[PDB]
Image (cartoon, helix red, strand yellow):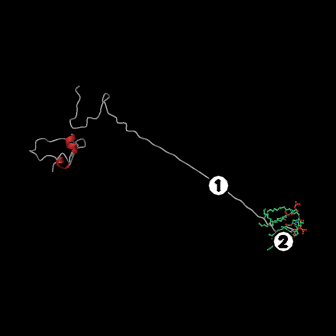
Amino acid sequence: NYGYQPLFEDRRPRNIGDTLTIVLQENVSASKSSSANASRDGKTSFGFDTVPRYLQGL
Amino acid sequence: ERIRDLTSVQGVRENSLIGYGLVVGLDGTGDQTTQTPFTTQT
Ligand SMILES: CCCCCCCCCCCCCCCC(=O)O[C@H](CCCCCCCCCCC)CC(=O)N[C@H]1[C@@H](OP(=O)(O)O)O[C@H](CO[C@@H]2O[C@H](CO)[C@@H](OP(=O)(O)O)[C@H](OC(=O)C[C@@H](CCCCCCCCCCC)OC(=O)CCCCCCCCCCCCC)[C@H]2NC(=O)C[C@@H](CCCCCCCCCCC)OC(=O)CCCCCCCCCCC)[C@@H](O)[C@@H]1OC(=O)C[C@H](O)CCCCCCCCCCC
């Protein structure tokens, strides 16, 4: 090979045949949450158990 | 006054070149490699 080569550079790959080292160190994490609620409660009462003579009509 | 002393030609122009290098010798007095990591790396 007659190609020029720098002395002080970091010897990065530059041509087709050059080799490079890859450190994967891949780490991905995704999360998703959702919630919903709805509560309705009702309860009504009414009773005499004793009615006046004048109110017995109703 | 000559034309050359007060005029420049369109095609004639200078350019700036920059580069990084190392200097050896110096009888000491060189970079402190502890505080200059790029020197040792180069
Ligand atoms: C937002 C506000 C808007 C305004 C709203 C207006 C009022 C909106 C309306 C509210 C009133 C509800 C109407 C109920 C009667 C009715 O029409 O709808 C019925 C179906 C229900 C639909 C209602 C959906 C509304 C939908 C909701 C709408 C809401 C908006 C059909 C029906 O008719 N079903 C019917 C049938 O059943 P069956 O199907 O099986 O056959 O027959 C059986 C057997 O009949 C009984 O027999 C008895 C003997 O056996 C006999 O006694 P006896 O003496 O003879 O012995 C006895 O006679 C008697 O009461 C004898 C005598 C009693 C006098 C005692 C003193 C009481 C004073 C009491 C004074 C009241 C004080 C407020 O009378 C009356 O003078 C009644 C008083 C009149 C007051 C007038 C108000 C002046 C304003 C005074 C104002 C005061 C100012 C401070 C016989 N009673 C009857 O006939 C029935 C009827 C005879 C009508 C002739 C009298 C003149 C009416 C003249 C005109 C009336 C017109 C309305 O009386 C009533 O209650 C009428 C009540 C009217 C109140 C309105 C208030 C207006 C405010 C005005 C406001 C604007 C009944 O049981 C059954 O009725 C029952 O069960 C009813 C039960 O009792 C009573 C439960 C009440 C609980 C509250 C409701 C709770 C319900 C809630 C859930 C929905």
Among the 4 quarters of the image, the one containing residue B39: top left
* Residue drawn where x is 41% and y is 40% of the image: A27
Residue A16, x across and y down, in percent: 32, 28
- Say which quadrant the N terminus of chain A sits in: top left
Residue B21, x across and y down, in percent: 18, 41
* Residue drawn where x is 22% and y is 32% of the image: A5
* Residue drawn where x is 14% and y is 46% of the image: B30
Residue nearest the viewer, comparing B20 with A47? A47
Amino acid at dot 1: Ser
Residue A51, x across and y down, in percent: 83, 69
Residue nearest the viewer, comparing B29 with A38? A38
Q: On screen, A8 above or below B31? A: above
The residue carrying mark 2 is A52
Q: Distance between the residues labelled 1 and 2?
A: 40 Å
Q: On screen, B13 above or below A4? A: below
Ligand 1 picture quarter: bottom right
Q: Residues within 10 Å of mark 1 (few under 14, many from 20)?
A: few
Q: Is residue A47 visible?
A: yes
Q: On screen, B26 above or below A45? A: above
Q: Mark 2 lies on which chain?
A: A
Q: Quick one: SS at disc 1?
A: loop
* Residue drawn where x is 21% and y is 38% of the image: A8
The residue carrying mark 1 is A39
Q: Which of marks 1 and 2 is nearer the N terminus?
A: 1
